[PDB]
Image (cartoon, rainbow, N blue to C red):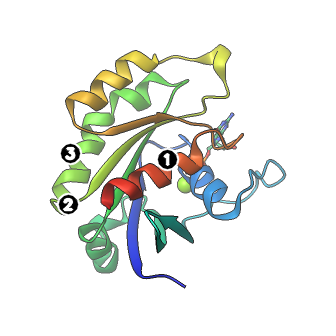
Amino acid sequence: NYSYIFKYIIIGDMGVGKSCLLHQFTEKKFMADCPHTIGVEFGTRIIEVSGQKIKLQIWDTAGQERFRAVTRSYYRGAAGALMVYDITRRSTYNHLSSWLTDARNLTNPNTVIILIGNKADLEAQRDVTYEEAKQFAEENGLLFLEASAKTGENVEDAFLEAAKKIY
Ligand SMILES: Nc1nc2c(ncn2[C@@H]2O[C@H](COP(=O)(O)OP(=O)(O)O)[C@@H](O)[C@H]2O)c(=O)[nH]1
Ligand SMILES: [Mg+2]
């Protein structure tokens, strides 16, 4: 049961963990025994926000908004956007202005955007600081969390904090 529907997109460079973040949230598990599959594209989950029951739809959109009319309008009705980079890979951080442009250009003026730095579990291999990403987020009025799709650290919060701001 639910009283509202929130559409989410999840975007960012290939291999940053978009499919894993979506899977960890909807199914509460990290695979590790299934490296041979493509990686989950879509999912849903009912959450409780501010005393309300809300259904979240989540789409690893993969740039299909340029080709598919239905993907085009889902994008235009997006309530939230997770913009994801890989903390161990600076190039994924460097492409954020491009992803932010797409996001804003192709959604609607209400769309709430959250920045996620994924793979926080790989501490020894950190390539991007918390501090620089926090300043990018603050400049652009985004929410910001460092998270780990593998361990589940801050993954629930990622989706829930966005939803509470959507009100
Ligand atoms: N260590 C670690 N590996 C991850 C994490 N999230 C994803 N991966 C791995 O990164 C690779 C790409 O993940 P995937 O979700 O398919 O990336 P996508 O292309 O953005 O959807 C896979 O081999 C995952 O097992 C994480 O939080 N920590
Ligand atoms: Mg994927």
Most extreme residue toward the right is 33
Real-space Cα distance between discs 2 and 3? Answer: 15 Å
Residue depicted at 46% across the width and 16% down the height:
129
Image height check: is 90 above or below 34?
above
Residue shown at 22%/62% (left/top)?
A: 107
For the point 61% across and 63% down, the residue is 40
Q: In this view, does 108 lie to the left or right of 137?
A: left
Amino acid tagged 3: Thr
Query: Height in image: 71 above or below 127?
Result: below
Kindly identify the amino acid type of the residue bearing the numbered disc 1: Ala
Q: Is residue 94 above or below residue 1?
A: above
Q: Tell me the kind of residue under disc 2.
A: Asn
| Mark 3 nearby-residue class (10 Å; few <14, some 14–19, many ≥20) | few
Q: What element carries label 3?
A: helix
Nearer mark to the viewer, of 2 and 3:
2
> Residue 85, located in which quarter of the rendered image?
top left
| Residue found 45% across the figure and 20% down from its top | 130
- Residue highlighted by disc 2: 110
Sequence order check, earlier mark of 2 and 3: 3
Which residue in the protein does label 3 denote? 101
Ligand 2, by image quadrant, is: bottom right
Residue 54 percent coordinates (x, y): 46, 73
Nearer the observer, disc 1 or disc 3?
Answer: 1
Residue under pointer 1: 158
In the rendered image, which quarter is residue 73 located in?
A: bottom left
Q: How far apart are marks 2 and 1 (CA)?
A: 18 Å
Do we see residue 152 in this rendering? yes
